[PDB]
Amino acid sequence: EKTRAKNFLIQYKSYNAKIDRSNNIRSKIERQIQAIEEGQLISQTGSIFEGIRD
Amino acid sequence: ELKYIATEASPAKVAEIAEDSDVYVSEIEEAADILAGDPEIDLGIDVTDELNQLE
Image (cartoon, rainbow over all chains, first blue to last red):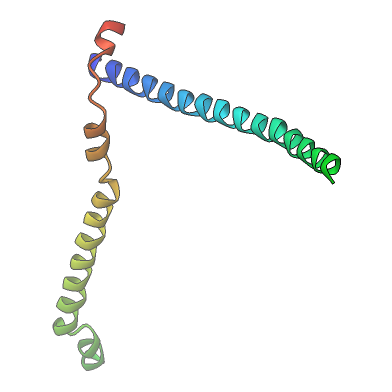
């Protein structure tokens, strides 16, 4: 039933793109958490240097 | 009593209510086939040859 066979193959690789869609969205958000971790400490560093100045 | 049966088995009304049913029947059944219209999308968006290697 090679028609149906390649159709299962069509539906088979139909998921793989969707898994990759997830993985890249995960990686993108992990990177954007880190920018709030690193960014948040930089912000406070700026305020004590303001305390030194005044 | 034959008069009272013939008032309400009137062939003027038998033929009306029989024609009305048939129109609604073809209305509903064709409204089931457009309810299965999506095969035209499935057969279109996926045409993937590459799996002949996978075969």
